[PDB]
Image (cartoon, rainbow, N blue to C red; front, side):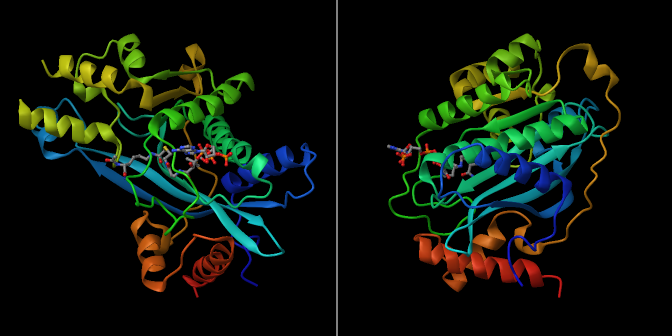
Length: 319
Ligand SMILES: CC(=O)N[C@H](CCCCNC(=O)CSCCNC(=O)CCNC(=O)[C@H](O)C(C)(C)COP(=O)(O)OP(=O)(O)OC[C@H]1O[C@@H](n2cnc3c(N)ncnc32)[C@H](O)[C@@H]1OP(=O)(O)O)C(N)=O
């Protein structure tokens, strides 16, 4: 059987799944089926400091030439009409306790995407928020300290993870998306999971940032390219602050631990093994496969069959 339930379980996936399904059992809605959360890819990578920042800070010995990270792809499936429907996907980057500064003990959400067929609709957002809260709660427990989110909707007609969204699935503008993250993080705060969250500009000020080399440097994040442009343009710190302030509302810095307890945390050890899966190594592979195979997520029926196809591929990549 090629169900989503039969995809390999992990501590991470199970923690998210248990959180979602406990939330759903506290709601009085008949329609809500059981949710499965599966980590489907997990591999170790490095992000290299791009040439401008490398010449300024790596060649002078002020900044590590690259940063190691674990990246993971996870997906959420709902039983709908007795048949799995993938409705949520997310990629994360995790910079562990051995990672050189400035990235040490930080997580970054590379990408998040969704297809709006969760039943019931009135619980869809709450379920997305619970998946994200669960993720923060989980990496906090392993000893990560700071999480990072860039609230950036896709360009028009573009897809982050799932090929071909429904035509009536509206795409939030950045303001709506910031507010969506604030509501999620406000709930995380109320549950005493996160200590605080701040926009990037306020955080940099309180951190007394004076050099671009102090900014966490993540793969595909906004800031590495900003820094490459400012070096081609040629007080780098004064510009950086002006850019951070200008876009501050869209960059979230989330603190999972605060205060002197940070100084006591043991090494971070991922209890889950790595999972080799070329299909879900980054976003382009699955997007390409679906485009070529005409797997769309644009109606419930097409999402059902595309989920079936995605599941058969994930179960047999290792055959
Ligand atoms: C730039 C660069 O260099 N590089 C970038 C890389 C940047 C880094 C990427 N950053 C991230 O990954 C984290 S930010 C999230 C960005 N990902 C996406 O946005 C994927 C598409 N969006 C979605 O899947 C969902 O909207 C989701 C974000 C999961 C929220 O779903 P939801 O359902 O809980 O809330 P709702 O969507 O607001 O809808 C909730 C209500 O709001 C409605 N609504 C939504 N949008 C609109 C709208 N525009 N106008 C009017 N109403 C609107 C909506 O219809 C609804 O109504 P109802 O509940 O009555 O039906 C690059 N690689 O391109």
